[PDB]
Amino acid sequence: SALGKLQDVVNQNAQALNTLVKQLSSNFGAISSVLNDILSRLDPPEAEV
Amino acid sequence: ASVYAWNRKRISNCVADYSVLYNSASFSTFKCYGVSPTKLNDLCFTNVYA
Image (cartoon, rainbow over all chains, first blue to last red; front, side, top):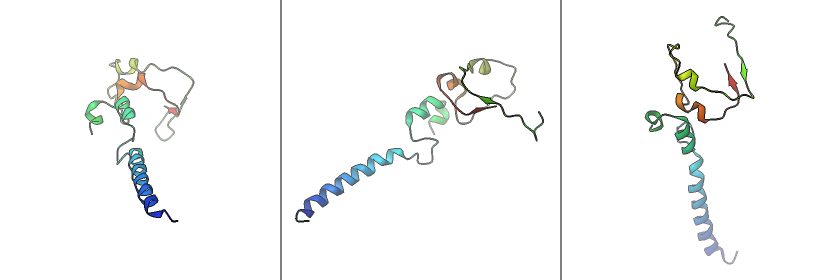
């Protein structure tokens, strides 16, 4: 644990990137989190929503 | 069948042409909810039930 100050910064940045990547898996109330699934399943009036 | 004993049929291991369902004018109501009616020929499904 001698080099914990640099490793803390590295872990925080990697964890922020992992959270930002993980947030793509959430649909945020939509029917799916995948854009290709919505664009291949729905007409543009409801795919817009 | 009647609505209290509504008949459920499994559809599996077939290639389905839904374009004859959209282009037919015999249906008074043809309303899809989670999918566009014109994209049904472009997708693959399982657990299809009528």
